[PDB]
Image 1 (tube, helix red, strand yellow):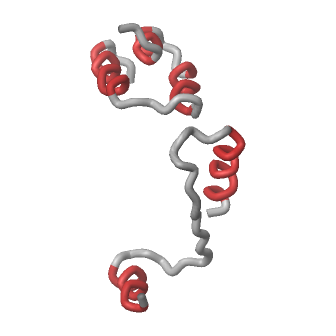
Image 2 (cartoon, chains in turn yellow, purple):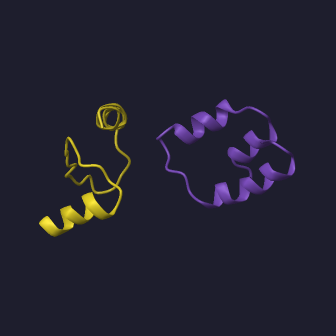
Amino acid sequence: PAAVYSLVTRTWGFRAPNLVVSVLGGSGGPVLQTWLQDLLRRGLVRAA
Amino acid sequence: YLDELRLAVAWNRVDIAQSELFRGDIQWRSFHLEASLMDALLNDRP
């Protein structure tokens, strides 16, 4: 993966990151209750 | 068939479309938008 990191940093115009969070879950696909939408709509985008 | 977005575009109120689109209670389909854009273009609602 050193090659693909060098690809993303060098060739394509992306800047090197400062913070890598990784959302990793499965709800199965119904609509989620409202405060989870508030959490992903306030905490993982404004900070990001 | 009467729906909500076409009735909102027939009026001039924007906040009804704001709440209906941004509200997460019902996931929106594609046919409603694809039909209602045709009525939005004709009556000059930019």
